[PDB]
Amino acid sequence: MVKVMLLGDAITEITCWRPLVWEQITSAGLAGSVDFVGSMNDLQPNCSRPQGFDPDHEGHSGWQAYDIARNNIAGWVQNTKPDIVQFMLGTNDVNIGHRNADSIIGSYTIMLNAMRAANPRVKVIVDKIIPTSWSDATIEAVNTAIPGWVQQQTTAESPVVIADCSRAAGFTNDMLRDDGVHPNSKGDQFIAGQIGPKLIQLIKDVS
Ligand SMILES: [Ca+2]
Ligand SMILES: [Zn+2]
C-alpha cells in the first residue's frame, strides 16, 4: 500500500479535486494500492464521491504554512508516516497572516525538513498556488520562487516535484468562487488534472 498525505488549507478541505483524483487513481488500476492518510476526513456534500473513495486528508481551512511548519507537520507525519506528501499552502499566510513570499518559502523548507526527518525517502509534490481573483502579487511571488526552491531542495533519495496549479498554467478567474480565493467546480477539475498525473507517477514509483 502507498500512503499519500494531501496536506493543505481550505483549497484541500472544502473542495472536490480529491474525489476527482481518486477517480484518476481508480482508472489507473491503483484503487487497492493507495491509502490517503491524515487527521481529517470531511468532504463537502456537493462533491461527487466515487465508489471506494478514501476521504482522509490533511487540509485545514484558514491554516497557514507558517503555523503548520512550526507546530503541526511533525506530529502529522509521525502519526501517518506517508510515502508521498502533496501540498498547496501559502494562501492564508498572505490573506490572513499578511506574510511575505520569503516567509512562505522558508516555511516550505521547515515543512520539507520535518517530512524528511520522518521519512528520508519521502516524495513530495509542491503545488504552485492557485491565484486570487485580484491576482495577489505575493501569491505570484511564491510561484516565481517555487522552481528555485525545488531545484535547491530536491534529491535523488527524496524527490520534490511541482504540480503547477497557477495562473500561468491556465487557472482562470472563472475557476474561482465569488469569494475570490476558493476554486469552484471548474477550478477543481483544473486542479485535479494538474495534481493527479504527478501523484499517479509517484505512486507507481513507490510500487
Ligand atoms: Ca486512508
Ligand atoms: Zn480515514
Image: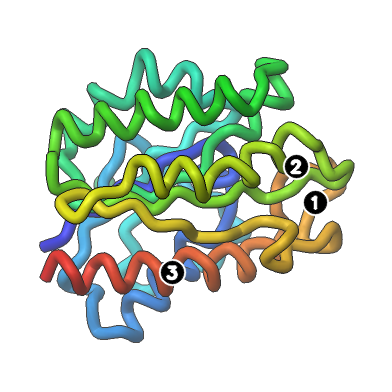
Mark 3–mark 1 CB contact (< 8 Å): no
Q: Quadrant of residue 40?
A: top left
Tag of residue 177: 1
Q: Disc 3 and disc 2: Cα gap in Å?
A: 21 Å
Task: Answer few, some or many: residues within 10 Å of disc 1's Cα (few below 14, many 20 plus, some between 14 and 19).
Answer: some
Mark 2–mark 1 CB contact (< 8 Å): yes
Pick whichever of labels 3 and 2 is earlier in the sequence: 2
* Residue 56 visible, this angle: no
For image coordinates 36% across by 14% down, the residue present is 71
Amino acid type, residue under disc 3 in the picture:
Gly
Q: Disc 3 and disc 1: Cα gap in Å?
A: 22 Å
- How far across and down, in percent of the image, does residue 27 sit? 35, 85
Q: Quadrant of residue 153?
A: top left
For image coordinates 49% across by 32% down, the residue present is 60
Tag of residue 196: 3
Query: In the visual, does 26 lie left or right of 186?
Result: left
- Residue receiving disc 2: 181
| SS state under label 3 | helix
* Residue 43 visible, this angle: yes
